[PDB]
Image (cartoon, coloured by chain):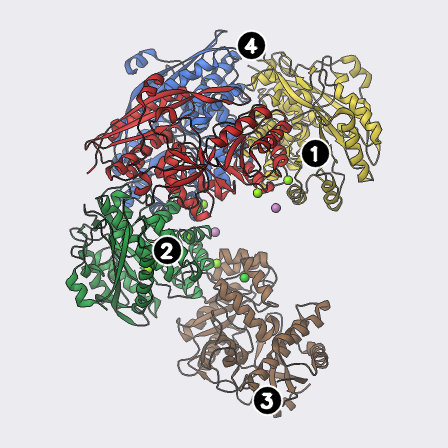
Chain colours: A brown, B green, C red, D blue, E yellow
Amino acid sequence: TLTFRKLTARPVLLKLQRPVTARIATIPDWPLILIDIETEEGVPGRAYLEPYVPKAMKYLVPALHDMSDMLAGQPLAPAEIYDKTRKSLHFVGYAGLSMIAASGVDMAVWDALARAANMPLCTLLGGTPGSVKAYNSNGLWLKSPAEVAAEAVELKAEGQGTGFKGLKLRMGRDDPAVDIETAEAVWDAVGRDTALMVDFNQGLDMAEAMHRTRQIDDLGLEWIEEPVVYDNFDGYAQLRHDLKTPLMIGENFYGPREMHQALQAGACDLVMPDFMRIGGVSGWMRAAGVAGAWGIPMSTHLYPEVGAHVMRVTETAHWLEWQSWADPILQEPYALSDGDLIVPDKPGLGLDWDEDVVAANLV
Amino acid sequence: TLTFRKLTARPVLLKLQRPVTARIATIPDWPLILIDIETEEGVPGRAYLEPYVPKAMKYLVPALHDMSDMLAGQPLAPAEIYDKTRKSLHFVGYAGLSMIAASGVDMAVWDALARAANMPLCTLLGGTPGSVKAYNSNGLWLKSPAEVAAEAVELKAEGQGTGFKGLKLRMGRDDPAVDIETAEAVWDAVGRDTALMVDFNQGLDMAEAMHRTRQIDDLGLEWIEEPVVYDNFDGYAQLRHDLKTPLMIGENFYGPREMHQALQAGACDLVMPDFMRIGGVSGWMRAAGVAGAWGIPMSTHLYPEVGAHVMRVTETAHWLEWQSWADPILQEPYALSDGDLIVPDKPGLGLDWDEDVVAANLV
Amino acid sequence: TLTFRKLTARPVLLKLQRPVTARIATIPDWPLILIDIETEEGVPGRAYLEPYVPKAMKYLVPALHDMSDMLAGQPLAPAEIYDKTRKSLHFVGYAGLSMIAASGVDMAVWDALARAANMPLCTLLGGTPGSVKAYNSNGLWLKSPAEVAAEAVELKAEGQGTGFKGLKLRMGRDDPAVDIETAEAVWDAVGRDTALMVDFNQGLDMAEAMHRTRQIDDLGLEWIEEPVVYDNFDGYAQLRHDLKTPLMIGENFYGPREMHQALQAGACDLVMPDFMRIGGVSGWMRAAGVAGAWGIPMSTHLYPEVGAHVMRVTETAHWLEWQSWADPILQEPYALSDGDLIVPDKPGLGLDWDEDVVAANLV
Amino acid sequence: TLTFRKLTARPVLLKLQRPVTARIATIPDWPLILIDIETEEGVPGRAYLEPYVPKAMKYLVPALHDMSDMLAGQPLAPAEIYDKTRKSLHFVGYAGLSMIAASGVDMAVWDALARAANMPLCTLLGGTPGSVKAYNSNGLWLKSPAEVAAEAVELKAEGQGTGFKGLKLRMGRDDPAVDIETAEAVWDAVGRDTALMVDFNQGLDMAEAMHRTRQIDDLGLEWIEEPVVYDNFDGYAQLRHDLKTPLMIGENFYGPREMHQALQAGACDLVMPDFMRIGGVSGWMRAAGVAGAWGIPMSTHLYPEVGAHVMRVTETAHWLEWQSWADPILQEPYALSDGDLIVPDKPGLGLDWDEDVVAANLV
Amino acid sequence: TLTFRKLTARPVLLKLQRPVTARIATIPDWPLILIDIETEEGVPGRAYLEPYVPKAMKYLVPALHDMSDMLAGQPLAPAEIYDKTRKSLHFVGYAGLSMIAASGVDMAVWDALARAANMPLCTLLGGTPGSVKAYNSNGLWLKSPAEVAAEAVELKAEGQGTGFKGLKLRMGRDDPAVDIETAEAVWDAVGRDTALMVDFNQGLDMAEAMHRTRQIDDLGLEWIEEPVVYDNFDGYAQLRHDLKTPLMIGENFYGPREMHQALQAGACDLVMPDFMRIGGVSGWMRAAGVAGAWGIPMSTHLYPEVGAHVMRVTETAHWLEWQSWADPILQEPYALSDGDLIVPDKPGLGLDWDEDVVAANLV
Ligand SMILES: [Cl-]
Ligand SMILES: [Cl-]
Ligand SMILES: [Mg+2]
Ligand SMILES: [Mg+2]
Ligand SMILES: [Mg+2]
Ligand SMILES: [Mg+2]
Ligand SMILES: [Mg+2]
Ligand SMILES: [Mg+2]
Ligand SMILES: [Mg+2]
Ligand SMILES: [Mg+2]
Ligand SMILES: [Mg+2]
Ligand SMILES: [Mg+2]
Ligand code: NI
Ligand code: NI
């Protein structure tokens, strides 16, 4: 047997190696909530959240400790717990901060059940450890073309061996021609065999989206990601239709049902759920089922360690989004080989906290 | 009157003249199940199955002999038999192996019925013997461009006289540019007036299909065949809308109803039913009713002899798929003239086994 | 071989045993065109048309003789002939009188082909002679409840043995209350386990149809047939939705494609093609593929002899519509046994003209 | 008051100045049926049918005279007579030869009604005589590119003055490249100012239609007309969507409801009802209500005189189709000026027969 | 020849025999605008408008007169006039007051055109004078049941002979249950053979409409008219779906295109255009072509005289709405016989102003 004892959630703030350079402002900081579960039987559980907004950690940590109090003494069973955490907060929404806290609990609980089985997570879910093809989203923010191009060479090599086969390139400069120029410069530096995933981060309104995505539709991008506000399914459907290049969304899906509603609306060619919004491992697995049936290629967003684990059992696995923003809190991040992330043969997610860096960065 | 006595199914394995060089592996062997029907009145029936997977014959031969036992003494009437054979295995599915056994019975009993009428099959079905425009699918597997271009010269010539007006060219190499290079080499060699039908054999996921089919959309191909796994109708609907070049599927339709559902789902521009999957002659004639109503051009897959006969009475007959992989077990294969297959003036399908090649290759 | 020599069309006009009593008038005469085909090899073909409008025989007999001149010396191949005949009249329409001529030729040609094979038509089409469940449409025209009920007793009795399991009851009286009263009086006389198929013969506009079909929706009818004008598909779709009782149409389908269109539009729950409009045996078999794919129960209209043959090989065979209106000119009408029509074991349709009744009624 | 007495239909076979050179054969002859109405009040009605196939006049004349007998003594009211002609043959189809007969009657009767009112037909319908822009469909059949280019010059000039602003060009040659060459050669000769309306005459199957219409989609055609068989609404919907050039159909619409169904199916961008199929003037004015509500531009097919009249009152009037195949039997064909056809200030249609030519070409 | 000289429009305010007794207030005044046309050739035109709102006549009279000035000297051609009037006010909307002015001109102009041809309007339109089934909308306002039942006996007798076969019963009392009692009381007094058309006059919101139309759906009403505000097509679609009783709208359609949109939206089972809103005779005729293609039973609203003329040529004519509100200003209104309005054998609408009643009620 396996019984939930308590959950501890510790907020930390990390200084990015390469700060987010958007048009609106520059963001140098990256918040993380570290989550440790204890069971009566002495099996630990470890995972983390990346909630983007440092301030919101002040709402999430309390919400996590409330969930811990609620769940104390009950079976550590991810699916049961997933149902209790959501119901507890249905009155203030299944989407949003409610889901975010519930997902954090979920990943840590799955990690604990896997350790209890003495299995890597992916093995518990019915696969095995192995490689997962990945792309580098460490940077390529809205700097100058020559700066971005030089960074692109570094980001590629971060993949080891032959390098990453893809890079995420951000767009949304005041002047569209520079975005193209930046894309053209990057390919000149790293070679055209490299896949470029472009991301607008919801920066455009529909009119801007139409003109701008059309300008880049014949560039040969791997995909065009979230050009408008994430819940505009009417707009996405129009864009998907006009665009030949694959249209990518999903990082803002709050649960499998929302994915299912996006697909019924014909809103996208590709999807990439985020682990804290989709409902953790449980939400992902259900979402993989939906994506599986529609046959839509499915990628990840953030959480490279959990992502690599579930991608090993995801029917339509497409790309794993890789970045090292969370690396400092880990004793050993997963190894890279030829741009492929390697799931290590360790129980659960195989995460161990670097407590020095944690203490040096606690809030 | 005409009465079913028994049915014999004999498994053979032929050495292909040109090995199937796919991406995963090279396949040198081609399995065939020879079917001989006996009636109480002495009228024989002869047809064959081409089930691809040699191990599968050990599931199909037993299934055929069980059908033989069940049919013994009953009237040799294809439409009644098609009903009893399907009904007997409905619990283990109408589609797949069940259908395949029922389709082999069906082709052979229609052979017997046409013999009993002393009519060629096409004539019993309401047409007459004649020629059917064909294309050559003997090869053009995944070898080098210069090697495929040379092989193409030979394949066109197998058509006799002015040769085949079309060739099937397989695509799916690791590097998409080499697929294109191969098409260009082939067209240089045999001339651009030669139609090229491109087949990916379900080897791509959706994202790969979107990119690769787009790259070849302006080449001038006759059609693009099964880019993705065959039951992904949502994906096919998408590909077909985006591609200007006709999208072709159908070889994995299990029955007319499945064809009808694919057309309702807007999955394809063209269809090419396979005789062992569609329900033999009975299935084909029904799918032809469906295709005729929609106005969808209908082509064949494998079984060039049965194909030529039914194509003579198919309202939307398009292209016949010709290969000579099964020729060795026949005393006389159908003649070719300028790329048309000639249906001979013989009762039934006019097959007589070469019992030397059979014994030389029996399993 | 088998070669078309000539075709002769003789118009005859018969006094109906039970005259058509509608609201507009009383139609007492039934026209038939008797078709005889000769081949160079001495095989005959015989079939007939029931074109409803006596004077229309002056358009069809010439049309049929014109087709005989065109076909002269060509192979007697039904599928090919069906192409040729329909093609020769395409400027004056595929639907309507053109189709009626082609249909007559088609049925007779199929009869000849089957004779050539020494097989009953149904056997040639892949089935066997046997029984086909029928219902009686000889009468139950718009008379008084008392009269209709007493006639219903005789009508059930024409079935032999336990009698017809179904009767066609015509409706469309000035006072709908009397239609209902009539239906009730019939069930009172022949018993409630007798299926009543109600036919309105296109007598109503949509508002009347909405009112009257609703009034009878709960009587327990077998079906409701053509309440409005036959090409009002928008209307039929509305009626079909509002009514729970099955809605029946199709006797005015000109070809399999038109059936396809009615089904896409959602116009009906059941279909009943007429052989002179659907395209004869060739048209029926195509439409049977379409109906089979959709799963729509398929019934016949007129031509009980051809009807019984093709229903033996029609996948979704429902009811055969039986009447004795053309019996007079046949030497041996098909036998009836417990309301089933018995397809006799004779070549083709096994029709032989009763020349005494022909001369007596020739036009 | 105005009373129908009798109707006379005279079959006539003319020789075309420029013979129809198609792919399959060459038709030099053009059948006509001159129709004459007599009224008890001494007012005549004159109109003609152009039924394409000479042999079909054998069916129509008997049908026309059968309608005379039926209408004799009844009020000469076009709408009432339209109702009564259709209903009399509904059993042998609303479409096809029956509609053709009714339309001929309908045109003569509308002509009589306009004469009785002493107004040109267009004036009776609420308009006034005037010019109607036309295009020349006299030829450009399937001849040598140079032969067609030369003819195109003569054709523009038949329009008088600055000439016809549009020409019908027939496509469908064995080699599609020569179709295009012909377009380019016709333009070289008459200037790119000239609109080209391409017509395939239903000569293609769907696969041919897809390839070929795509090849000509960037040529700058005014429209592409009936590429495939006229009732294939599913195929037309696909072509319309794939093609940017407008897709024209409708010359084979039998009645206003059929146009309505085509538009619901998304079958076309432009329509061009033919007066013998659409139901004469009654049918046209109803069709114009439909096209007017959809906003679909409506053009005509054959019958330049009736055509010019109704176009004057057609809300979405587009192009008139002009040809002079019927000219010989008219004393005074309508005047041409700078491409526009001039509706004269004569009562009715203003037709008078040249009884010399009639007698010379009677049957 | 026929030329427009001037149009005079005279406001008159009558006092209804039976005052309008709605839920909100009682309305005893009925405004009419009388319209007279002068042609250069001395042919007159007479028709009237019923704008409901007395003060509106001050917007319309200046609008009609402004139209007179612009039309001065141009040909009196309804179709052409219909286009010029509508065009001149397109900047201030095609629907609404613009249309109402244009419709008044259109009816008066068609009257003149018919007079100039010495024909009744219906004869000019292809019909003949005759009877048209009518229903009585003179009263049955929101009084008590026994009062309404009493008035009903009176209203039915106004139809002469066997009486009106239909009555319009208004609903929308504060208390629904009394609406129901009123229907029964009317039926208890005039017999259940009499059709009741129920009109709510847009008086409900959707919740009330759902509840109240449902409560009366089993009463046996001829139809249910306009329960909610007239432009709520979403709501009507729902109501029409839920209600088995036919749902009637249309009196508020501004033009044939609006009817087309309503049908496309599935908004109703029946339509009843109003002549000032639909576009007079021109708009009606076009709308009749639309309605005719759909098979929608079409009825009239107000203007019994113009209505009876067009109903004689309306393919799906259903019910004529008859009331005697405008009678006082006519010398000889149309006769009734057994509930059928009689179109008299007189040129145009046969309207002549009783000028003493006009002088007596002028504004
Ligand atoms: Cl789903
Ligand atoms: Cl279908
Ligand atoms: Mg992103
Ligand atoms: Mg797209
Ligand atoms: Mg294939
Ligand atoms: Mg496509
Ligand atoms: Mg019937
Ligand atoms: Mg239903
Ligand atoms: Mg044409
Ligand atoms: Mg288009
Ligand atoms: Mg009202
Ligand atoms: Mg309803
Ligand atoms: Ni599109
Ligand atoms: Ni429903």
Q: Nearer the viewer, mark 4 or mark 1?
A: 1
Q: Image quarter for residue A32? A: bottom right
- The chain containing the residue under callout 1 comes to E
| Residue count near mark 3 (Cα–Cα under 10 Å), binned few <14, some 14–19, many ≥20 | some
Query: In the rendered structure, are the residues bearing label 2 and label 3 in contact, judged by CB atoms less than 8 Å apart?
Result: no
Q: Confirm or reject: label 3 Cβ below 8 Å from ligand 3.
A: no
Residue labelled with disc 1: E220
Helix, strand, or loop for circle 1? loop
Query: In the rendered structure, are the residues bearing label 4 and label 1 in contact, judged by CB atoms less than 8 Å apart?
Result: no
Closer-to-camera residue (B95/B317): B95
Which amino acid is tagged 1? Gly
Labels 3 and 1 within one chain: no
Labels 2 and 3 within one chain: no
Q: Confirm or reject: label 4 Cβ below 8 Å from ligand 11.
A: no
Q: Residue at x 43, y 34 (%)?
A: D250
Labels 4 and 3 within one chain: no
- The chain containing the residue under callout 2 comes to B
Q: Nearer the viewer, mark 2 or mark 3?
A: 2
- Above or below for E89 versus B210: above
Which amino acid is tagged 3? Trp
Closer-to-camera residue (B227/C89): C89
Closer-to-camera residue (B63/E12): B63
Which amino acid is tagged 2? Thr
In 3D space, how far apart are the residues under numbered discs 4 and 2 (Cα atoms)? 73 Å
Residue labelled with disc 3: A353
Helix, strand, or loop for circle 3? loop
Residue labelled with disc 4: D1
Q: Position of residue E173 (x, y in %)?
A: 81, 37
Q: Nearer the viewer, mark 3 or mark 1?
A: 1
Residue labelled with disc 2: B85
